[PDB]
């Protein structure tokens, strides 16, 4: 009874505890996961409303209809959101080209983008969310990166107050310090200085809690970030996550843990290959952020297999090894899947994934979130309200 | 009830749950604290038997009795274990000199030091212990520091194997860079190469799990530590622990976390006066090792107060701030107190400390231990068996 992730599970009757240990059903437990309080740690602001009906809602409320770009032709791959074959990362970023840099530069569009995304987290029962944005991408000749960040913060801080404290999601912001291919270390300096300033401007409500080192790949300009000077970042309270995408080495991961002092790892799908790194990543507490849909589409994994094969999703292996694994959505729009579909696609990606392990990935995320003491106790008190099962008759 | 540390406490009757939240009593709770499955993270091998009956049980086992040095007369202060005035740190170390490097160069005395200490951990109901030692301090012209360490390891492993699994204390070894370091980078290089080699020799039973950078408290050896590459230590899997304490050098602790990648801080008593550093130490999980008796005897703290002041023992503040705080013995011999007596003294150091806060320091210690997945899965299964209270009210 001392292996349950939350203390409230121990106070259940044996009928339900026996139910927690059976495999998750991706066709019947759709309603139990939905009511579950989730925790999002990898969500990109500029990828929420990329195509469909939400893209029109964002483009409709623009403050400069004349400035809005035309909606270019972005055809989704067939079988979407489960493509016939993977599409890659470069070809995956382009599906969200109807929204982002060239759309959200409109102050009006940014309001709907930040307010429609909060309504998508609330609908999903998210209790905590770290949103990732690049304010320097949405700036113009009259709106500096600090002005855009001011707006983004208060757009989420406004939605957070118009919501009852019982169902209120808590949104925090991560500044994606992108390793620009075309931009130089000037871009990094501005990004790291913007987070250090924001990391002390706000102490309550929406806060800038860390920096996301996207572009950690490209081990040719190695690294323009391992020069670092990240010590100011560490002394102001900020936390570092490395967006280890599009790469299959282990040396970068080693240097992110011990030179960058990173606390989370993004899309670290090849950790089991090196068991020495896997043991360190599990004893130091480093958290691994996995995105089921975004990974099945960029990389592609076997679906509905009946055995843990060689090329299977590493979620179950990570859990066995002790790694603190979390499940996220990456791009809500670009992947067309909410935080519930991703936790339900796990049943088909990892054969045998128990529905108790789902609660473990949520308890892990609750410990890997860059929240403060007040924010944690409010998050812990909301995951303690785990809903009771739906179908236990067999 | 989400605040309960141990999932097993959720299954207690509502009558007892209120008992936990009541303040601890350093007298009537002895039987309950004495039976708690405890975790030891700061215990020195060379400070176990410095005086008394134990000091002679060790000397009476040396293979070369004639080689034993004469038993000096070390006068313990009056009041001891609880002095009416602190004796400083340098006096504290000299207080134990009938044991340690001078005595434990004999294979017979060393064998009786690693087995009498294991009997003190069992008598105290310890389920996990990390013991720190300096093999190079006990080496002779014919006994290499690796020969000493290989003997120390097998004395504990042979003691652990002879005890039933359900009552067995798991002992792990930390290699300590002695406080007299920095002089030569040759000795800190032989020290880190011994741990990298030991961290691969043994993968089961008693293991070398980390290195303890003592002397960090000094400035001429803290730069030698910052000039030495610790990267090979991190790749092997060894963890790093640093001694804080008398030196209230905030800059030292900052660099020990982000340069040496330290996971634990020893005697970090001045963290509250640095609110910025107390947030990083409380959000990253860095654990703080506190020694209630070794801290009352080296620094001195108010006892039996009624309400918090401005200089009381910071264990209450640390816990509120979210810091992961552990309680240990430091030197079990030099201080006449076991792990049970250090937990009970917190009731006098910290006014109003709750019986649930005591059980938290043992869950914090369990998460701070440098044990692996197998060791951890067996330590949780022993902390979950928390004894039920005696009176209940
Ligand atoms: N999968 C990924 N791999 C690498 N970098 C990524 C990835 N996803 C996002 N990024 C980085 O995040 C930065 C911010 O992207 P975001 O999704 O917030 O929208 P955006 O800046 O409006 O988009 P874009 O530049 O594609 O039009 C991008 O510039 C890119 O550097
Ligand atoms: N409070 C402390 N602060 C700093 N260093 C300490 C403290 N207590 C012990 N040490 C260091 O711990 C190291 C190991 O001490 P231990 O108790 O194991 O005895 P020892 O070194 O074998 O004994 P001896 O000093 O008789 O040779 C010593 O080198 C000492 O420098
Ligand atoms: Zn991403
Ligand atoms: Zn010590």
Image: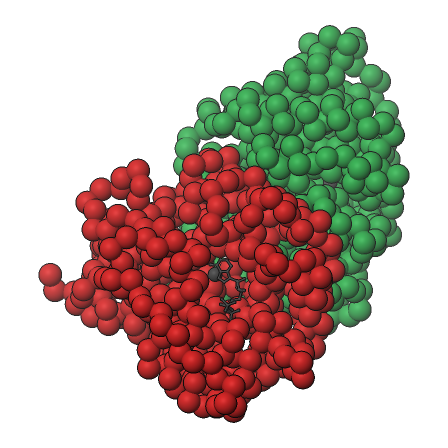
Chain colours: A red, B green
**Quadrant in the rendering for residue A145:** bottom right
Where residue A158 sits in the image (x, y, percent)?
53, 87
Residue pictured at 26% horizontal, 48% vertical: A302
In this view, B23 is above or below A120: above
Where residue B244 sits in the image (x, y, percent)?
77, 48
Which quadrant is home to the N terminus of chain A?
Answer: bottom left
Toward the left, the furthest residue is A394
Q: Is residue A18 visible?
A: yes
B148, A255: nearer the viewer? A255
Residue pictured at 70% horizontal, 57% vertical: A185
| Left or right of A189 in this view: B150 | left
B183, B124: nearer the viewer? B183
| Left or right of B309 in this view: A268 | left
**Quadrant in the rendering for residue B351:** bottom right
Where residue A151 sits in the image (x, y, percent)?
59, 83
Where residue B29 sits in the image (x, y, percent)?
56, 56
Residue pictured at 49% horizontal, 73% vertical: A100
In this view, B351 is above or below A163: above
A76, A285: nearer the viewer? A76
Residue pictured at 80% horizontal, 37% vertical: B227
**Quadrant in the rendering for residue B114:** top right
Which quadrant is home to the C terminus of chain A?
Answer: bottom left
């Amino acid at each position: 009874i001392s292996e349950l992730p939350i203390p409230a599970l121990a106070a259940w009757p044996p009928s339900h505890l026996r139910w927690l240990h059976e495999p998750l059903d991706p066709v019947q437990d759709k309603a139990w996961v939905q009511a579950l309080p989730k925790v999002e740690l990898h969500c990109h602001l500029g990828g929420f409303a990329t195509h469909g009906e939400l893209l029109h809602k964002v483009r409709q409320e623009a403050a400069n209809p004349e400035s809005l770009p035309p909606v270019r032709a972005i055809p989704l791959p067939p079988g979407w959101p489960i493509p016939e074959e993977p599409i890659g990362l470069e070809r995956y970023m382009r599906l969200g080209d109807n929204n982002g840099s060239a759309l959200l530069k409109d102050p009006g569009c940014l309001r709907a983008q930040c307010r429609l995304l909060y309504e998508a987290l609330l609908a999903d029962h998210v209790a905590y969310a770290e949103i990732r944005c690049s304010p320097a991408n949405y700036a113009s000749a009259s709106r500096s990166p600090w002005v855009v960040l001011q707006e983004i913060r208060n757009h989420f801080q406004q939605a957070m107050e118009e919501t009852p404290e019982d169902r209120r999601c808590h949104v925090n912001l991560l500044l994606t310090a992108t390793r620009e291919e075309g931009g130089d270390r000037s871009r990094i300096a501005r990004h790291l200085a913007l987070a250090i300033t924001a990391a002390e401007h706000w102490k309550n409500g929406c806060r800038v809690v860390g920096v996301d080192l996207a572009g950690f790949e490209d081990r040719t300009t190695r690294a323009a970030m391992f020069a670092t000077d990240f010590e100011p970042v560490h002394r102001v309270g900020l936390a570092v996550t490395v967006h280890a995408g599009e790469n299959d080495d282990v040396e970068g991961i080693w240097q992110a843990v011990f030179k960058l002092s990173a606390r989370r790892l993004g899309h670290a799908l090849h950790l089991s290959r090196s068991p020495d790194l896997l043991r360190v990543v599990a004893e130091r507490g480093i958290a691994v952020e996995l995105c089921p849909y975004a990974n099945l589409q960029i990389k592609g994994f076997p679906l509905d297999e009946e055995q843990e094969g060689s090329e299977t999703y590493p979620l179950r292996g990570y859990l066995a090894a002790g790694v603190a694994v979390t499940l996220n959505t990456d791009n809500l729009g670009i992947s067309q899947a909410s935080l519930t579909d991703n936790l339900l696609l796990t049943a088909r990606l990892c054969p045998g994934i128990t529905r108790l392990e789902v609660l473990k990935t949520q308890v892990f995320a609750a410990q890997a979130a860059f929240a403060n003491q007040a924010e944690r106790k409010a998050l812990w008190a909301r995951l303690a309200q785990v809903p009771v099962p739906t179908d236990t008759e067999q």
